[PDB]
Amino acid sequence: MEDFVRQCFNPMIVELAEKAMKEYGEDPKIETNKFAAICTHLEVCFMYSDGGSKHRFEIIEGRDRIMAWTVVNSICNTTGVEKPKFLPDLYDYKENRFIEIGVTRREVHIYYLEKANKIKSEKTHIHIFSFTGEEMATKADYTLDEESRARIKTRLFTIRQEMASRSLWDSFRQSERA
Ligand SMILES: O=c1ccn([C@@H]2O[C@H](COP(=O)(O)O)[C@@H](O)[C@H]2O)c(=O)[nH]1
Ligand SMILES: [Mn+2]
Ligand SMILES: [Mn+2]
Image (cartoon, rainbow, N blue to C red; front, side, top):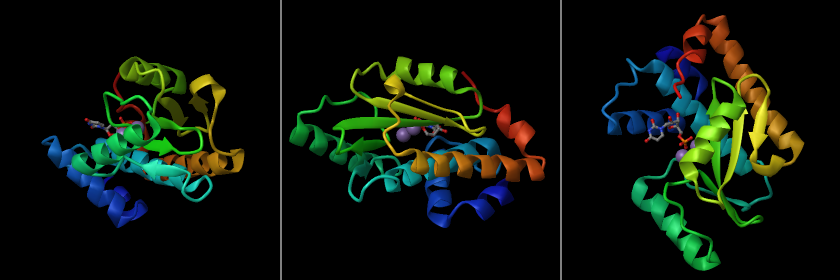
């Protein structure tokens, strides 16, 4: 799985993922499924932000904490949008809302609920993707056009298929906890 990650995700993604794990005292070489999940989520966040019109989205995920909150507090001051308790993943300038993105190895509905329970904030939009084509978003509002989403869903299927071809999928699939 370590070899799979370093081979299928670009170096910037892999570097951010390693940083996040070490910030929690975890070793990417040991908790390899977590390593793959973090890379995957980062990749989805970056694809999502490219999926709109130019400049539609601000990326919050992937930034160090100081810069992330700088962006968030700057957006809140400028738009008067409510300040979230937790860093979200993106801001949508067109819809004037933050977005929390989830990628789940389980089922989209359960993950969506966990995310909602956690945010509790009324304003932040939630969008969940799975590795088997399914998605779920707040009030069935999927934000991007279906072509953009299809490309995200297809990339995730492609990752699943790759892990499976290497016998990594069984372990990976069963590694997400409530
Ligand atoms: O404190 C944290 C926050 C997030 N994550 C992981 O980073 C990825 C993205 O988190 P989120 O933006 O969906 O909350 C997920 O795999 C999640 O479990 C952590 O390990 N620790
Ligand atoms: Mn995040
Ligand atoms: Mn997220």
